[PDB]
Length: 105
Length: 105
Image 1 (cartoon, chains in turn yellow, blue):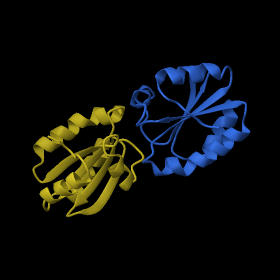
Image 2 (spheres, chains in turn yellow, cyan; image 1 turned 90 degrees about the horizontal axis):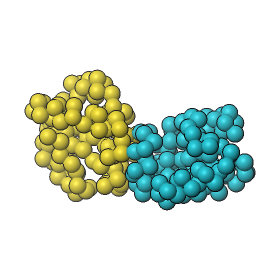
Image 3 (cartoon, one colour; image 1 turned 30 degrees about the vertical axis):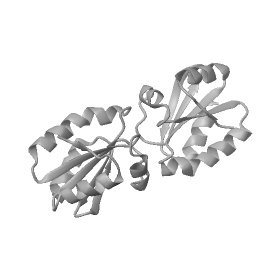
Image 4 (tube, one colour; image 1 turned 90 degrees about the vertical axis):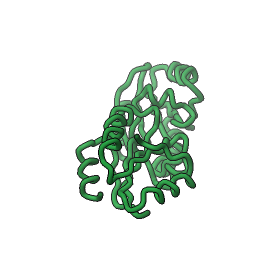
């Protein structure tokens, strides 16, 4: 399952909850076609990889978070670990996403 | 002038009012850095080019319109004439925008 970040305080709580695990955050919009296409794949990844935490942020719901993170394309995947930004991926490229997960987890 | 589209009906009304003119639509978000970066240049261009209609759509206000046009990367510039799609440009590239206006005006 992919947890939807509710606000900025919630984002910090989730990053804390993740512990030492790589966190992958999907910045998406409900009007974004590629976002919807890849969402089930993220759910499957979320279900199967126990050493990675998957989150999602609806940019229309958390516009402050989208701005703070300089989102321009949907979907954007942010890769964090122990509160540090490790990488970013713009677009629904599942292979590159998987590669960044394997590289950073 | 760059007019802000209020909803789907308003979008249709503006497309009709353009008559035979090229219409350029900027799909943007208020949390989008490059969007804000290029907005003043679009405003300047619109004040000069009276034979081209310039519109803008806030994807947060008009999510339905965003979905209709398959917006992914922002800002997206859609080029239309007589209600029909001519071209599309993702990202804030001013030279490419001018090339596409020159091509389609």
